Each structure stands twice: as structure tokens, then as C-alpha cells.
Amino acid sequence: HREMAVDCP
Amino acid sequence: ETHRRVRLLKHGSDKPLGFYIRDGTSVRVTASGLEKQPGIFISRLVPGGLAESTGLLAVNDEVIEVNGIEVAGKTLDQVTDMMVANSSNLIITVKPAN
Image 1 (cartoon, rainbow over the protein chains, first blue to last red):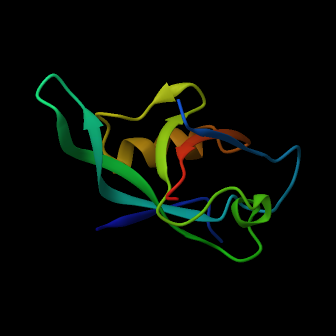
Image 2 (image 1 turned 90 degrees about the vertical axis):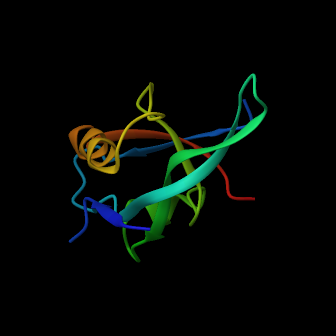
């Protein structure tokens, strides 16, 4: 499973 | 349906949303029966971010809609883009893992 970040510092 | 409407309202706050989403498989109803279809799920919650601070979002929860728009049929790049677009007042509807 590939992932992606929603508003991360 | 049996879903939770969680809202990550900022109201002029720095604190990021601080969560990730990923590709997964969800089971939905059809005329054929129960089918495995592509889904979008919560990867993890960043410490300090607003997502964690709610206590309602959890890992492996399924994203149903983003601010009124169902994400079924959409790719991960699209859903990510929907969420960061609405990032000030984001409203997620999820199906809790448990």
C-alpha cells in the first residue's frame, strides 16, 4: 500500500 | 449509514492536519453480492497534528467523503488533492476500522 501526506510538517 | 463525520476545522491555526492516507481494499454491496473495490484509508496520525487531537480519526479508517464529495472511484492523488484543497476546514466522513 502506497501512502500520501495531507498537510504534514 | 454507520459513518462518522469528523471535521478538522483550523480557524486560523498553524497546527497541521498531520495525517497520511493510502490505497486499500474495501468491500461494498452490488447486485452480484459483496465485492472488493479500491478504497482510501488512514495510514497514520502525526503526533501534535489536529487529526490526532480529535480522538475520532484512527489508523485503517476508510475515507468515505471529503466535504460532501464521495471519494469512491477516485485515485489517491485526487483524494489527497481534495483534502489539501479544503485543508482550512476539512470535513472527513469515515467508516471506523472497528
